[PDB]
Amino acid sequence: MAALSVDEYKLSREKKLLLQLENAETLLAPLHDAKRKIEQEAEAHTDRVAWAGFAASGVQTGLFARLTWWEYSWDIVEPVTYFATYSTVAATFGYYLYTQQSFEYPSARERVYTKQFYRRAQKQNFDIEKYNRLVTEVDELRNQLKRLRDPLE
Amino acid sequence: MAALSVDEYKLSREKKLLLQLENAETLLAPLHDAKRKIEQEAEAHTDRVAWAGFAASGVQTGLFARLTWWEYSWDIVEPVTYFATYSTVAATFGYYLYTQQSFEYPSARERVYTKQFYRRAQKQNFDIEKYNRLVTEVDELRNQLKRLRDPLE
Amino acid sequence: MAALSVDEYKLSREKKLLLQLENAETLLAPLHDAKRKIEQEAEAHTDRVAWAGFAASGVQTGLFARLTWWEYSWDIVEPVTYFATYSTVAATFGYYLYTQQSFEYPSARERVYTKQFYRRAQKQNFDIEKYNRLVTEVDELRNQLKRLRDPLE
Amino acid sequence: MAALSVDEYKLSREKKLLLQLENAETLLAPLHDAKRKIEQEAEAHTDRVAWAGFAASGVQTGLFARLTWWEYSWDIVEPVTYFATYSTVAATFGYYLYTQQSFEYPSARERVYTKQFYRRAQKQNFDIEKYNRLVTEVDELRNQLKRLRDPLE
Amino acid sequence: MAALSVDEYKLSREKKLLLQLENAETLLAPLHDAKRKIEQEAEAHTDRVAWAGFAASGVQTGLFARLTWWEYSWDIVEPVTYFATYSTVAATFGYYLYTQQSFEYPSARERVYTKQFYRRAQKQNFDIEKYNRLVTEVDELRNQLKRLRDPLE
């Protein structure tokens, strides 16, 4: 009585409460809030949108070339700007990557020793996780109807 | 004389109506009605697409430069509109921001102490809120069949 | 001299029919054909898609200036097409407003009492309408289940 | 004992089978096979992407024009490729009409308004048909509870 | 125990496990679990957006042509970036076939018996498949109700 818990040693100690508890674990909004806090080292998304950063950096050498072209023709304007438009379509790929960005972020090393683990960082949630995971709560009502079918009369 | 409700009342002690009331809260009509009351904030969104307004403002004075060195070649026209095209792709980013724009301000003043009654800026959605929350009505389904599974033997 | 409905055809076997009818009302196919007609009368918001026409039409007169100063250089082509690329995104904004454009009419003119309120019968239809309304047919499953829960044999 | 199962009460005949048969029709797998049969005539969609086919056809004759007036100055390159990008945005619209195309697909075969009428027939499916139609199989569970709710359970 | 299942239970033998087994086939996380583990080999799509790879290869050599006719004018630069941009809109189509590729790959080289598979391909499934397939688990829920419904009434 001094110890007290919910797991181990049972005798129909309110079965209805345990099924209600299983539903709360499936929603796991608490853990989703912990991913939002990570705002500091969160640049793990920016580095994938930075793929476009190397494309525009190449022209920096090209600006010296307009100064040289004073014998070719000179008329060659717009090079820094056409490369900049190519970067904006790169912004468009990002519509898909939104939730998934958490999957590539951890190293999943574990080989050379270990440390923390109570953080995971492989969910984020705002839509993909919310729809698949909560309809899966349906899978729990499929277990309860299963036993109703064996007795009747 | 009615039809949407047979007789006065009988097979309804108090409990069935309360559960029906939980479904009305899940749909979220009140909070959706609140979006109609402040509707004028639709300009709060046009202030985020204005990020693009500073990009075109840089060259606008640049027209004066063509007048200044008219002898180099002149064939250097086209600069003000091509920066305007960079703004046109910015209109495309907007597919993300409609339902999400309400999340932008809390992520600078989220708090937890007292707060505005019990709300959480859960406005602006017209689709993400409607589908996810309604399947949660199936969560309530799981509470009623669990009691039936215990008797019948 | 009746026989279609007066006696026997509704002795005490109408409650089962009432649940079958409630699911049928949510499905609504007769009324859905009336919603489809709005796509013709949708000419209201097409004035906001026509924004694309005035942009490209205004500049055609600018090209005439190339004919007046034909000696400056001439190499200045392409201006009518860059405004046209801006028109190409206008097709891109379209998929979003497509079902939703109906949202403007329910607002009703300044005259309360009777205006197809709650039932709407004038809102959107092509894909947001079927998904929301039929999963609600499942919410009726939650109502029959509760009266089913009171029993115990 | 020598039979179909151990017992399961011999009183099925066809009714248990008939509800199971309704679920198989609902998934949509043979009607989907019908989409495979017309795969050679599925080029019917190109007629709607051809709305843009007129945009690229304008300048196509223009290539002959740079060669004829080569004396003015020259330096007018790049016209054909930017018009080609305008055709690619038309490819982006293609996600709206893709599953729906079954409505426009008949053509050059209509007079008495009606056509086909071989049990509606959508003769197309890859995502919109599959999602809506199967949550409707859940509507059929709404019928099974209605009979259980009339006795005890 | 070195025999029988993991752990037994009262009023069970194999029938309770068999209904759970139908649910396990619908879930079949295995192949979906394999997609996160092999993420590096996910280049199975990078060969589909390559359809456009032949478009940019044409002008790449074209730079040499500016050197051959160096007296025409020279102001003919800029061809390579707009053709490269034509490939990025090809990335935009990429959102349609992206998970679906799983259906096409089997219909090309089979003869399975190994384990490592030198073919280097497998079923993706984690968004179009996960949402529809899982609610189908609710279809088995419709089967339980049929059998408790027939004995009483």
Image (cartoon, coloured by chain):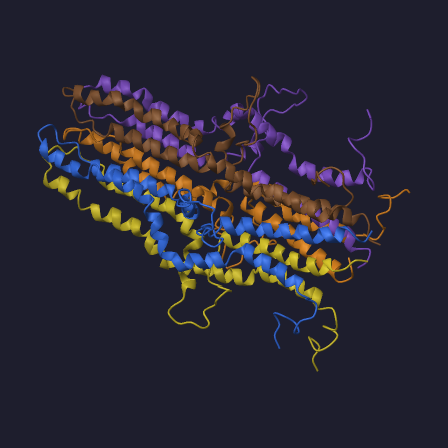
Chain colours: A brown, B blue, C yellow, D orange, E purple
Residue at image x 81%, y 52%?
A: D13
Q: Residue furthest bottom?
A: C1
Which one is in front, E73 or B125?
Answer: B125
Q: Quadrant of the C terminus of chain D?
A: bottom right
Q: A56 left or right of C112?
A: left
Vertical side of B3 occupied by D72: above or below: above
Q: Quadrant of residue C21?
A: bottom right
Would you say residue C85 is visible in this rendering? no
Residue at image x 44%, y 35%?
A: A39
Q: Residue furthest right?
A: D1
Which one is in front, D146 or A34?
Answer: A34
Vertical side of E147 occupied by E61: above or below: above
Residue at image x 41%, y 45%?
A: B109
Residue at image x 48%, y 44%?
A: D98
Would you say residue C26 is visible in this rendering? yes
Q: Quadrant of the N terminus of chain D?
A: top right
Question: x and y percent of residue D54 in the render?
Answer: 33, 42
Q: Quadrant of residue A46?
A: top left
Question: x and y percent of residue D143 in the render?
Answer: 69, 57
Which one is in front, B143 or C4?
Answer: B143
Q: B72 left or right of C30?
A: left
Question: x and y percent of residue A42 in the render?
Answer: 44, 32
Question: x and y percent of residue B148 in the render?
Answer: 75, 53
Which one is in front, C68 or E99?
Answer: E99
Q: So how many labels did they put on this image?
A: 0
